[PDB]
Length: 152
Ligand code: NA
Image (tube, rainbow, N blue to C red; front, side):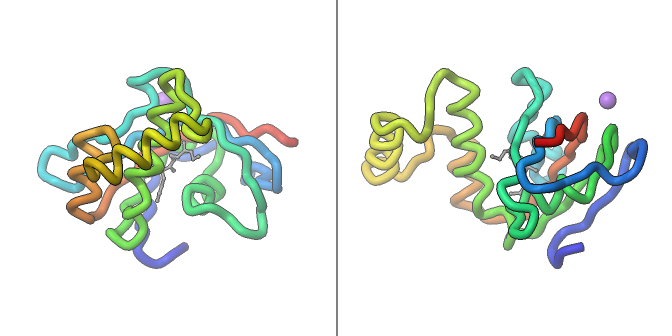
């Protein structure tokens, strides 16, 4: 448990806690929503396509999304409300997922240059919804569905 984050389980997982060691790969679906009346969806892995797949970089120093994932069991579906303090990073993080969904490598030099240039010129991440999210810091809910943990 971390401050500013409420976990709710909507479908209980199966089995013992996955082995969430350094280098293991987590396959999951997720949906991100505002906390407005409509619960406006910001991103939805199922809608766009295939599930996300991340590698735990270091079990001893977890990324924020790893803090979420490593609390989960296979097949679990949980909703995590995260206060404004945890979510200011989400728009750039979504930016980068969205470009990888496309054919673009956000780490390639021409892509990253264009991003910084448009961001300085136009104060934009390339996406109206993420821009409005960054201009208005606020809570988000992430619903995550954990599908599979693979050993390294
Ligand atoms: Na399901």
